[PDB]
Image (cartoon, rainbow over all chains, first blue to last red; front, side):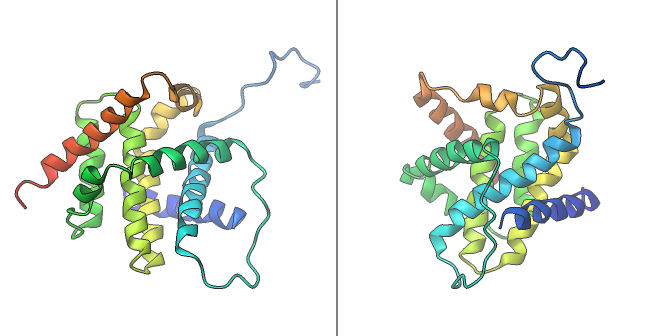
Length: 20
Length: 192
């Protein structure tokens, strides 16, 4: 989808900055 | 009281969103590990809390080594270098649906996609565009939340992946992954 990808993009960054 | 109750080794908590969260972490590890081959920008500060989780660590290990080994074949390597980076979303969407049309839950369609995705990420990274790097990741998770999550939950999380990791006759598995990638590419590069 489009909206879903946005939230997931945020989740990906959410965990990214959690370990880096 | 609840803990004092009879529990067979562990429990059964909601792993629906848990699996999704794990995916975001998995993608990070795989990208960060391979991004180190580019160097950096002088880490004067940086945030290194040290990966506490060993689950994602182990998963990234096998993925990294396999993905790295899948670059030995210069044949397939040059084939990827002959791709058309015109429509990033369309290319990704095509290969996503391509290995979905048959509905073959061979698992390989997922690991093969990971190699394709990482190749694109590395390519974009070589173009010095962090923005696109975040976009590709969003697309990867997009398809995951779309339908993949339903299959991962059914198999009891990443247990299926942990059980898919074999060893005997791995050579055929290598050819299998290569073949799947080749197939989609054959339908993509239709003379142009």
